[PDB]
Image (cartoon, rainbow over all chains, first blue to last red; front, side):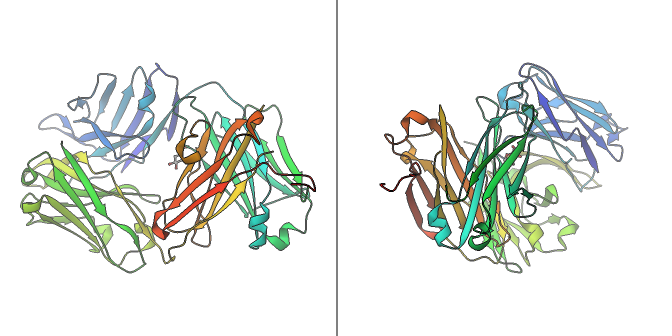
Length: 217
Length: 226
Ligand SMILES: OC[C@H]1O[C@H](O)[C@H](O)[C@@H](O)[C@@H]1O
């Protein structure tokens, strides 16, 4: 069992990131003084790429800013002078036995100063309502950090279980996120109420922001 | 030059079988073990199987209960993974990987130094279905979009104005709904001054259902005229 920490890390460009891997059993072999541990980098949408073997030996092509260290059961990957392309999920892997396993991964993202979301609400289209369903969409655009709370209120009643959220990958250029929250109701239920509101809480907002509309306006 | 090109996979019904394949180029295929590794929500990154250079010996993760089978065709630089009796926990991304290592009295030890691009495997009873595409009508910055609802399987592609509009576009990852169908939105922010003079059209393509939709997104009208 390999346990990485932290689960996620935000690092300012040019600064240093350190990821930890702890093994439940020693993987230092006394006879050759080697540690049977590898590190991998997985950029969004790509396969993992091998970076380090024997805990500290960079494989061909890997720059010195990626440094593996540790011994026995406690290992670390240090990324100095973090670059935009280093945002990725990093995994350790042991090969001390014939049953190789990976750690759970540590996600490294680019840190930036807080940016509040711009918030937009969309009523269902008349086209959709014809088909018997009503989707209401709340958009939170270009914010940082990723953590945000979105709550739906219908005629001031907090909704639960009838919305789903999606978040983008960190934007390559401005390092922000966007998030959609979609409330789904039957046409009949949608027409039972007037005020549709999404309430957004975010570190960048002094107090929650509410965007609303009245059905039919 | 040196690469692994994966094919196969896709949708498979629960309890059915699926074949995955991997084509090697740029290196001496018969000098390497090959392995398969998957990534799933519940189990993370998981080694599944390896196969020796000549194909005569195979080793599997016991958690698979014998359901998977690896083989290789050295004459044609191919390696295969056959999934059997698939279950929902098998949904994920499957990778073939070159397995760089060595053997001793105690077993085989190796790292994965070259990987294929990954193939998505989706275990589901859902029938192929094209999306419904609905406008997210706008309103010094305005937001607009398209809701791409109720399709199966992944993926859909969304462009704006045939690809002429890329700045400010965010196409969200699909979410799986309780119906077993996917949904996503694509949004773009644009100058308010452009509404009514600039045309905005989302182009949605869902190849599995042969669906192509071009949806004009227009500012909502409030009068009796329109
Ligand atoms: O915001 C980061 C996230 O972006 C999207 O949601 C991706 O689908 C997900 O894999 C990633 O973790």
